[PDB]
Image (cartoon, rainbow, N blue to C red; front, side, top):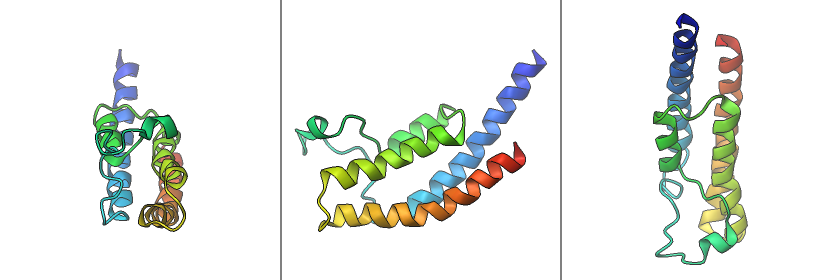
Length: 121
């Protein structure tokens, strides 16, 4: 149908906008602490602690499959990155501190993304 196409064009454009958001959030992680999945070879007990691991490469895979239907779903995954880290790692670690800085800096980007998503529809 023509409606299914129009819906698919909306999803494609959302994917465009979320790709730019993702790039901007990932720039706020210059140490690349959140770039890849925590290694189960190197942290073999991780899944005993963290039930839903997340990282920027995994989000990018979902993004490119047009797997985010709305901004809420994308934000859920970004919040998992931060929240998982703040639980597994102690306050006095470079990892925890990196997550706090990513959360704080990302807030700004996500605030305007929400306005754009609502604005453009």
